Image (spheres, coloured by chain):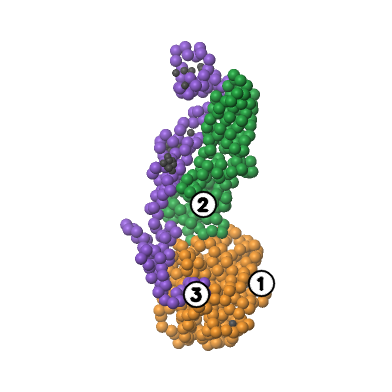
């Protein structure tokens, strides 16, 4: 047998899946995940896939730092994954502009408060519920010349010239972060 | 025990104190009224085999009370594969001349089944190690029974996380590391033979034996314990056997 | 899309990219600027990866750039919610829910057992002491 390698975390909005190599040839795998002081919990028992969904475990506490390892079968050979702290590393999904209403000389651009995989009371918490104040949205618009705005909520209130039509695009951002601080730009919307 | 705390009297009921000629020798673990599991190396320099005593219900070596029960050790069984002066197969099964009385202060630790221990107990992060050993490397032994919670490591991690040294003992499949590499906590020489007990769903089980390590709580090193799961069958078969004429007995392993 | 002579008319996002499928060039004629056209095109032409209905067992698909995300129902997990959480009753998985010993059995459910001095309760998973001083229990704390 050969130990797995290139263990990588694929996480967006807390949907976290561990991936690895190589493509199993006469060998199966079993994944174990834990917190530094917690017990090891097994997942994807004897799977032949080269991936393992660990979402249900990490959403139990997104602020904890998890370590996972992949056991190889024809103590067993294994490889550790990098440490993973959900709250600080899960990628922010592509946002969606929910709407925008013009009121005189101003426009209110609202950003959809998308849900995450974090469960709570039989429901999925929104990106706002999870990050609270650590999350802000940035607006990149233009008169149809670049313009930008920032909000700590899910809405932007900006000035617009009467008659002219504008186009908008937003990004979810967690300023305090060091890695994956921003999501990709949302689709472009035009009034 | 380095960096631990006193085990409140009665909270380490399976802990055994082994003496030779009345002198402190090693620790041990009671697993039933007549049998005690300790470390093989504890007997490397024993001359008077008829003077080995096992004390149960001990706590404070400077005060005597009614929870103490002494028993002559009628037999010391060591694997034929163990070599004095070394570290592999560091385990000994001791038969007490007379069974001890089970009380609130004298209770045996459970010897688990092999697969349960390998598949479940081995992945419980923390376990307790205890004894009246040195409080510091090269220091004095303890008067009151000490206990410490240490995390277990798979051998591959132990090796990768330990300072690569010269030709030191190898970590075999009959051992496992546990503890810390920052020089703060670990068991020590005088704790040898004592239990490495694992708590799982309301019950404690014997998973290891204080065996060896480079110094005690040495930066870049972990304590090493005999991997008891490898000896479950060996132990069970011996406990069902008849005693031999002499005290020392070497039984084949496997 | 382009119909006979429609290109005589000024560019319209609504008539061209919303009510119809517009090519990159058509999009470029509306937005003009290069970066603006690309910012729009990346999402417009990405295609909805949720179209295949990849999320199994009643899960909900959430579209993303060149990917998707499956939100599963409580009793399911996996990239596509393909894993049945109620079908993992095996010994390696949290000791099969057994309080003490666990034995697997192909074809049927795993069974639980206990160490000497304990008996398996009616629930088939728990173990209760059958003696006064069972192993592994600390009297003064019980
Ligand atoms: C360094 C001498 S030592 O500190 O006594 N370590 C030796 C092994 C050992 C380790 C390392 C080397 C070594 C060799 C080359 C280069 C550097 C070091 C050599 C021997 C060692 O541990 N030897 C055994 C006895 C061997 C016998 N049958 O007589 C021993 O002392 N056991 C008691 C013990 C219990 C717990 C710990 C602990 N948790 N911490 C440490 C020790
Ligand atoms: C639906 O389309 C996506 C595109 O990525 C594919 O990954 C799924 O397997 C399919 O069901
Ligand atoms: C999407 O989310 C999943 C979990 C289910 O609740 C579906 O009914 C819903 O559409
Ligand atoms: Ca005493
Ligand atoms: Ca057209
Ligand atoms: Ca057109
Ligand atoms: Ca056109
Ligand atoms: Ca229309
Ligand atoms: Ca048309
Ligand atoms: Ca053109
Ligand atoms: Ca054209
Ligand atoms: Ca898409």
Q: Return the chain for callout 2.
A: A
Q: Can residue A104 be seen in this view?
A: yes
Element class at badge 1: loop
The residue that mark 1 highlights is B136
Give me the chain that's green.
A
Q: Where is residue B234 in the image (x, y as percent from the top left)?
A: 44, 73
- Choose between A188 and B75: the one closer to the eye: A188
The hue in which chain B appears in the rendered picture of the protein: orange
Say which residue appears at 57% left-offset and 30% top-offset.
A109
Q: Which mark is residue A60?
A: 2
Q: How far apart are the two marked residues, 2 and 1, measured between alpha carbons?
A: 40 Å
Q: Name the secondary structure under disc 2.
A: loop
Label 2, label 3: how far apart the Cα atoms are: 34 Å
- Which residue is depicted at the point 55% across and 84% down? B66
The circle on residue C139 is: 3
* Chain with colour purple in the figure: C
Q: Which quadrant holds residue C121? A: bottom left
Residue at position x 32%, y 58% in the image: C108
Q: How far apart are marks 1 and 3 (CA)?
A: 31 Å
Q: Position of residue B74 (x, y in %)?
A: 48, 85
Number of labels in the image equals 3
Disc 2 versus disc 1: nearer the observer: 2
Chain assignment, label 1: B
**Marked residue chain, label 3:** C
Whether callout 2 and callout 1 share a subunit is answered: no
């Amino acid at each position: 047998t050969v130990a797995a390698y290139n263990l990588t975390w694929k996480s967006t909005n807390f949907k976290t899946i561990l991936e690895w190599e190589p493509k199993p040839v006469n060998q199966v795998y079993t994944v174990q995940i834990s917190t530094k002081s917690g017990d090891w919990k097994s997942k994807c028992f004897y799977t032949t896939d080269t991936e393992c969904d660990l979402t249900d475990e990490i959403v139990k506490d997104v602020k904890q730092t998890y370590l996972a390892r992949v056991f190889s079968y024809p103590e067993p050979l294994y490889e550790n994954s990098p440490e993973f702290t959900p709250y600080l590393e899960t990628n922010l999904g592509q946002p969606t502009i929910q709407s925008f209403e013009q009121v005189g000389t101003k426009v209110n651009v609202t950003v959809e408060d998308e849900r995450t995989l974090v469960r709570r009371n039989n429901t999925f918490l929104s990106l706002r519920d999870v990050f609270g104040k650590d999350l802000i949205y940035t607006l990149y618009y233009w008169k149809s010349g670049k313009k930008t705005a920032k909000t700590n909520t899910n809405e932007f209130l900006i000035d617009v010239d009467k008659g002219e039509n504008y186009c908008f695009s937003v990004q979810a951002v967690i300023p305090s972060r060091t890695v994956n601080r921003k999501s990709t730009d949302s689709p472009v919307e035009c009034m | 025990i380095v960096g631990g705390k006193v085990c409140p009297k009665g909270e380490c009921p399976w802990q055994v104190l082994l003496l030779v000629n009345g002198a402190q020798l090693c620790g041990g673990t009671l697993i039933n009224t007549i049998w005690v599991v300790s470390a093989a190396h504890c007997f490397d320099k024993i001359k008077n085999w008829r003077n080995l005593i096992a004390v149960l219900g001990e706590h404070d070596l400077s005060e005597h009370d009614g929870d103490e029960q002494s028993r002559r050790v009628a037999q010391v069984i060591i694997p034929s594969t163990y070599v004095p002066g070394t570290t592999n197969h560091d385990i000994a099964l001791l038969r007490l001349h007379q069974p001890v009385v089970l009380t609130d202060h004298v209770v045996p630790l459970c010897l688990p089944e092999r697969t349960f221990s390998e598949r479940t107990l081995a992945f419980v992060r923390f376990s307790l190690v205890s004894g009246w050993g040195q409080l510091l490397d090269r220091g004095a032994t303890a008067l009151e029974l000490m206990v410490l919670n240490v995390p277990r490591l798979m051998t591959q991690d132990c090796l990768q996380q330990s300072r690569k040294v010269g030709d030191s003992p190898n970590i075999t499949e009959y051992m496992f590391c546990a503890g810390y590499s920052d020089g703060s906590k670990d068991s020590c020489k005088g704790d040898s033979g004592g239990p490495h007990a694992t708590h799982y769903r309301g019950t404690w089980y014997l998973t290891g034996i204080v065996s060896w390590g480079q110094g005690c709580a040495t930066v870049g090193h972990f304590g090493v314990y005999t991997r008891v799961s490898q000896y479950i069958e060996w132990l069970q078969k011996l406990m069902r056997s008849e005693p031999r004429p002499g005290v020392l007995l070497r039984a084949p392993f496997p | 899309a382009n119909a006979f002579l429609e290109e005589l008319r000024p560019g319209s996002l609504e008539r061209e990219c919303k009510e119809e499928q517009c090519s990159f060039e058509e999009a470029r004629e509306i937005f003009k600027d290069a970066e603006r056209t690309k910012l729009f095109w990346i999402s417009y032409s990405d295609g909805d990866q949720c179209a295949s209905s990849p999320c199994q067992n009643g899960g909900s698909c959430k579209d993303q750039l060149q990917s998707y995300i499956c939100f599963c129902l409580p009793a399911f997990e996996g990239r596509n919610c393909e894993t049945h959480k109620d079908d993992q009753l095996i010994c390696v998985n949290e000791n099969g829910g057994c309080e003490q010993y666990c034995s697997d059995h192909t074809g049927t459910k795993r069974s639980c057992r206990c160490h000497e001095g304990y008996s398996l309760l009616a629930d088939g998973v728990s173990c209760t002491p059958t003696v006064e001083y069972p192993c592994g229990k600390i009297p003064i704390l019980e």
